[PDB]
Every structure is written in structure tokens, then in C-alpha cells.
Image (cartoon, rainbow, N blue to C red):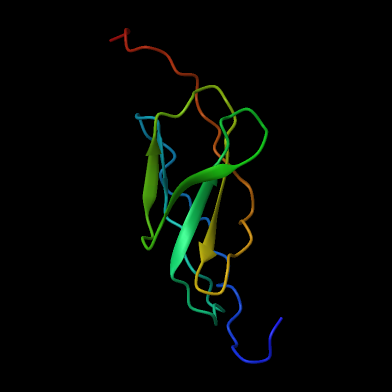
Length: 110
């Protein structure tokens, strides 16, 4: 480290999943900064696995506080996580958020 500049990574965002009970197959993410967030953030990076249970990759990144993904498999567990990033570096992923998807069946009954 150095002894000149002082600015630690931005406080990790809080996964406030709200969009869960929907007809479509899109998981809207609307995280939020903690009440103790002392370090300002410049952006946030999203991550989600391919419902396989391996490694997490980047899905979105910017300066917004609300982003959703389209085209999500059904009857398959999904693990997502959002983090903050700025000039400093990058914050650690949040608490693994599981998005239990309901059995996907074509629209027939009615």
C-alpha cells in the first residue's frame, strides 16, 4: 500500500431483491448502499451463474441502481451477487442471493 492517497473500496451494496413474483423470466436487481457507507461509490458490478453451480461472471456494470436480466432458465437454482466499484478498486460480492425459479411451462391452459 501507499501513504499518500486515502480511499478504501466502496461499501458493498445490499441485495434488496423485489422483483420475484412475476410472469416473465427476468430478475430485477435493486440493491442499495448501507446506512454506514462512509466511502462513496462510482459504480456497481453484477454477477450471475448459468444455473450450473460453477463460477460467477459479470452480467452488468455502470452507475445505475436498478438492472434486470432477460432469458433466465426455469426449474433451476440461480445465484446472483452485486458489488460496488470505484477509483479505489472493487468491493466483495454480497450474500449469495438464490432466485428459486418456478417450473417453466408453455401457455396452454385457459
